[PDB]
Image: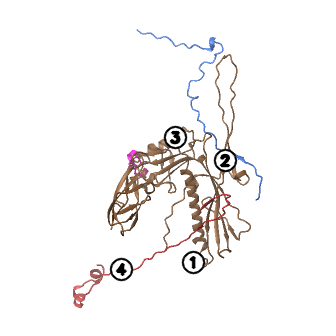
Amino acid sequence: IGVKQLQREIVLPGLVWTNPLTDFGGSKNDTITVRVPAITTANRRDLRDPDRTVIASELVEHSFGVTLDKHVYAALKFTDEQRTLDIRDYTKQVLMPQVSAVAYELEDYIAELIEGAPYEETILIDPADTVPAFITADQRMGEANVPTDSRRLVVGSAVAAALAKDKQFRHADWSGDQANAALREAHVGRLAGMNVIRSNAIAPDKAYLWHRTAFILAYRTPVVPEGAKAGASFSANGVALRWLADYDYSQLGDRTLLDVFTGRKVVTEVDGSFVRAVELQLQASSITIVGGAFALATTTGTKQLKVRDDNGTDVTARCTFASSAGTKATVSAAGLVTGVAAGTADITASYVPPQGGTAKTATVTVTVP
Amino acid sequence: AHIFVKPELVAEIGVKQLQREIVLPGLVWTNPLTDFGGSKNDTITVRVPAITTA
Amino acid sequence: NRRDLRDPDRTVIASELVEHSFGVTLDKHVYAALKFTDEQRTLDIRDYTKQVLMP
């Protein structure tokens, strides 16, 4: 029998505008220019005014550019000694992991696109009541006259858990769902008029709401060259990758490459302000080091600390660590603690909250043997 | 190396400048008076009837 | 991995496929044993499948 390694699901590639336009090859610098049609301004005169001149309006079309600028690949140095030696059923022991790796890389690419956008403010989600934050997000997207259809909402694991824990969705009288789909099932489905899609690619304590015309992904399958011994077009989650395999030379072993050309764009407005998507972050109030007080294996032992906020989000990568007594044990900037002498020490973790202000502080005791 | 000559390919993919919806004109009392031409200073007077107290 | 398009540095970073395994081994002997003298088996025990096997 076999147990698979734990790998996340794939949601993002289906929720993003993909290949609106093609034929990047027949354009200068591999850029397609998208034309935004013009709008006009009117004017107001006064009746029976002695001067009879009219202010002539203007009709200026705008434009932006979409470009292919990245090339995602998963190369394998598949030495021929390994082939027919340990690798059996090539179609499932190497090809499937390679395809899955490229799919996960594309999902990470889209996730970096979505998270890395010019969001001028972040909408704070109060864990006690979360609906006001989502209603505020809807209101923000309504102030920009964004269409109300084809709006996608993606929430991290922490936000979904907080929504389920919210008394607004958990108490039946407060939600009107006399089946408690947030208590029997741990799944709140619809709120503030938008569906919920759970993802782990995005940061755990963040949610993003975007219109369809806010992010653009452009894909191109590389053409299988004539001089390639083995070529195929193994597909992916809506993407057609290209797989090509050299057989010899250098090491007299196989070398495989599974790749696709990719490009991203965030559709900003004509004034360079991003209003077609909004982001929300879960408000945090306290942090605690998981595991509490502990002891190391040796005097020079190493243990990797982990800090969770009150919402369960791990904030290890976002915390500053200090040691009360470094002569007995010191703590790195990434949470790793190494002992240098026998005895106890006190470690302080400081985390600036998303809402801002005084950082939350959590103190733990480490007893190096 | 190789040098190619290629167009620009301006495209339209449905991205348009965002505009407000129009809901106000159908809500206000429009055109109860029309004969503005046949009146002095283009002004039509409206007469509110008298009321009295006992 | 990802690389820039039309990059003159035409190199590819190879990836690694490592497959692990772990074992489950037998280490305990769960037993229940009953010893009956011949008199006990003859006289004292009246119904074997109810007085001995079931417990």
Does the residue at mark 1 contact the one at mark 3 (Cβ under 8 Å)? no
The amino acid type of the residue labelled 2 equals Gly
Q: Which chain carries label 3?
A: A
Residue A269 to residue A308: above or below = above
Mark sitting earlier along the chain (1/3) = 1
Estimate the x, y position of residue A83 in percent, counting from the top left: 61, 77
Q: Closer to the observer: label 1 or label 2? A: 2
Residue nearest the viewer, comparing A361 with B10: A361
- Name the residue carrying label 3: A140
Estimate the x, y position of residue B9 in percent, counting from the top left: 73, 48
- Magenta span covers which residues? A163-174
Mark sitting earlier along the chain (1/2) = 2
- Name the residue carrying label 1: A86
Q: Which residue is drawn at 71% across and 71% down?
A: A229
Residue nearest the viewer, comparing A182 with A49: A49
B3 left or right, relative to A60: right
Cα distance in 3D space between marks 2 and 3: 26 Å
As helix, strand or loop, the secondary structure at mark 2 comes to: strand
As helix, strand or loop, the secondary structure at mark 3 comes to: helix
Q: Which residue is drawn at 65% across and 31% down?
A: A41
Cα distance in 3D space between marks 4 and 1: 34 Å
Residue nearest the viewer, comparing A309 with B39: A309
Specify the quadrant of the image occupied by residue A368: bottom left
Cα distance in 3D space between marks 1 and 3: 57 Å
The amino acid type of the residue labelled 3 equals Arg
- Name the residue carrying label 2: A65
Query: Are callouts 1 and 3 both on one chain?
Result: yes
Query: Are callouts 1 and 2 both on one chain?
Result: yes
Q: Which chain carries label 2?
A: A
The amino acid type of the residue labelled 1 equals Asp
